[PDB]
Image: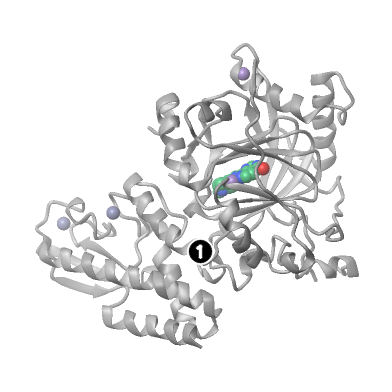
């Protein structure tokens, strides 16, 4: 068996004027949508980006998936989009003994939840998942030195074209210098019946926007950001192995009815072709594909997200989880470009920078009281990430760190001064990006930009 479908998530149908700016629209819907974690966006009827691709020239190697509930999963032949589709269609039609399009969505959903819970069933599927590249590019029009049709030119500069969304001025991941390919570049998902995505949240508690270009629906389950710890507590009791590198993170499939039984609010939707799904910061989400389909997704960060981004990095520290990027480095990068930032962006960055400076000042005073006296300026941004992670908590260091000549190349963040080595702290060196005197003018530049 029995499945009680969770209540439906909000569906928005913006007008052209509302649709015109994705960021102003996401800000408008946020009070409603953040209460459900996920929402669906139906674009104006006439917004129809052209989808064109050669099914024989598009190649990928899919991931094999064993459909088992509470079974740990990490975050196989080569197929063309054509041969994958043939396999995907034969699979669904043989599973149900029905034409591929006559299978009710409610039936596929009930069946998915039955098959993941039954030990006797050994059903395996395949899923295509990867970043856009020369072998398999974006489903949206992109500028290329091929000639595009006026229908493609129309959607080239759209804020809803997922290639543009990250590099817009209302976004904050945009300004990031560091190569963070997994968080700025769109991901492409080629689905089949029952291929799925386990319960998870985005890196740095970012938003995600997901578009279904074509094919059969994608079924989603979402949990609001406020219920994140409640969901984790439920998952700790039932699947403890999941909790006990970044490319080694464990996720699992769990029936939304189990979460609902433990008072976790869960919402669902069937995302159809031509619709967007938006996930909000720290909103847990999972789902599965109803059949052969093609989706494109990207992470993004608004001004509203900046304080949550800081809370996230603090949470990663307590967990000893790796960061994708340094949040402080991003803030300081934007402060160094204050003259060209959007005024609302400059105002929000300035508020986060005031918190960063005050926390940094307290941390530096604390390490000085531990007897760390020597200091030297260090350009942290020049170091590869693997060269500037705290030995204890794995945080990406930017503002400051402690080193000892006895452990060359090793760093601790300022919370973990006692975790570096057994030398007395007078042997340590405080490595810092900026003095407090360099930071106050950077914050003033933001204030002047915001006050204009
Ligand atoms: O339809 C989907 N299919 C697959 N995955 C999905 C997904 N997420 C997949 C990631 C990972 C995170 C890790 N990075 C690296 C690679 C991407 C994050 N969300 N969310 C929503 C929907 C889907
Ligand atoms: Mn099973
Ligand atoms: Mn996701
Ligand atoms: Zn640390
Ligand atoms: Zn030492």
Q: Residue at x 50, y 49 (%)?
A: 282
Question: Can you name the residue that lies furthest to the top here?
Answer: 120
Residue 75 in view, yes or no: no
Q: Give the left or right position of residue 53, taking residue 121 as reference.
A: right
Q: Secondary structure at mark 1?
A: loop
Residue 442 image offset from top left, x and y in percent: 38, 82
> Is the residue 241 above or below the residue 391 in the image?
above
Query: Ligand 1 is in which quadrant of the figure?
Result: top right
> Is the residue 23 above or below the residue 67 in the image?
below
Q: Give the left or right position of residue 57, taking residue 27 as reference.
A: right
Residue 396 image offset from top left, x and y in percent: 37, 58
In depth, the one of 308 and 378 nearer the eye is 308
Q: Is mark 1 within 8 Å of ligand 3?
A: no
In depth, the one of 211 and 296 nearer the eye is 211
Q: Which image quadrant: the N terminus?
A: top right
Q: Quadrant of residue 143?
A: bottom right
In depth, the one of 110 and 72 nearer the eye is 110
> Is the residue 135 above or below the residue 147 in the image?
above
Residue 408 in view, yes or no: yes
Residue 259 image offset from top left, x and y in percent: 51, 30
In depth, the one of 366 and 267 nearer the eye is 267
Q: Give the left or right position of residue 420, taking residue 423 as reference.
A: right
Residue 432 image offset from top left, x and y in percent: 28, 71
Colour setting: one colour
Badge 1 crowding class, 10 Å Cα cut-off, few under 14, some 14 to 19, many 20 or more, is: few
Q: Residue at x 81, y 59 (%)?
A: 44
Q: Residue at x 89, y 66 (%)?
A: 151
Circle 1 sits on which residue?
304
């Amino acid at each position: 068996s029995m499945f009680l479908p969770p209540p439906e998530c909000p569906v928005f149908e913006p007008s052209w004027e509302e649709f015109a700016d994705p960021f102003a629209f996401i800000h408008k819907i946020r009070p409603i949508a953040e209460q459900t974690g996920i929402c669906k966006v139906r674009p104006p009827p006439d917004w129809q980006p052209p989808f064109a691709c050669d099914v024989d020239k598009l190649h990928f190697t899919p991931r094999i998936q064993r459909l088992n509930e509470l079974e740990a999963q990490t975050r196989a032949r080569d197929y063309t989009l054509r041969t994958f589709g043939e396999m995907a269609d034969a699979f669904k039609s043989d599973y149900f003994n029905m034409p591929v399009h006559m299978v009710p969505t409610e039936l596929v959903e009930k069946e998915f939840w039955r098959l993941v819970s039954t030990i006797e069933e050994d059903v395996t599927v395949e899923y295509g998942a990867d970043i856009a590249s020369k072998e398999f590019g974006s489903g949206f029009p992109v500028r290329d030195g091929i000639k595009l049709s006026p229908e493609e030119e129309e959607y080239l500069d759209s804020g809803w074209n997922l290639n543009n969304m990250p590099v817009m001025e209302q976004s904050v991941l945009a300004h990031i210098t560091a190569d963070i390919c997994g968080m700025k570049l769109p991901w492409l998902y080629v689905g089949m019946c029952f291929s799925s995505f386990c319960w998870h949240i985005e890196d740095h508690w970012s938003y995600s926007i997901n578009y279904l270009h074509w094919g059969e629906p994608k079924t989603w389950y979402g949990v609001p950001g406020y219920a994140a710890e409640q969901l984790e507590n439920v998952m700790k009791k039932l699947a403890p192995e999941l909790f006990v590198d970044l490319l080694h993170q464990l996720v699992t499939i769990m029936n939304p009815n189990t979460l609902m039984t433990h008072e976790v609010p869960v919402y669902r939707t069937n995302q159809c072709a031509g619709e967007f799904v938006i996930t909000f910061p720290r909103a847990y989400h999972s789902g599965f594909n109803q059949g052969f389909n093609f989706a494109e997704a990207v992470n993004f960060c608004t001004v509203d997200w900046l304080p949550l981004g800081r809370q996230c990095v603090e949470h990663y520290r307590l967990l000893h989880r790796y960061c994708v990027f340094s949040h402080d480095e991003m803030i300081c990068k934007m402060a160094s470009k204050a003259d060209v930032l959007d005024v609302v962006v400059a105002s929000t960055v300035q508020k986060d920078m005031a918190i960063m400076i005050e926390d940094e000042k307290a941390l530096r005073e604390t390490v000085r009281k531990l007897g760390v006296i020597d200091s030297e300026r260090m350009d942290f941004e020049l170091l590869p990430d693997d060269e500037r992670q705290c030995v204890k908590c794995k945080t990406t260091c930017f503002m400051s760190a402690i080193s000892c000549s006895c452990k060359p190349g090793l760093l601790v963040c300022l919370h973990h001064v006692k975790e570096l080595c057994s030398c007395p702290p007078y042997k340590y060196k405080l490595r810092y990006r900026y003095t407090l005197d360099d930071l106050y003018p950077m914050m003033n530049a933001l204030k002047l930009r915001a006050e204009s």
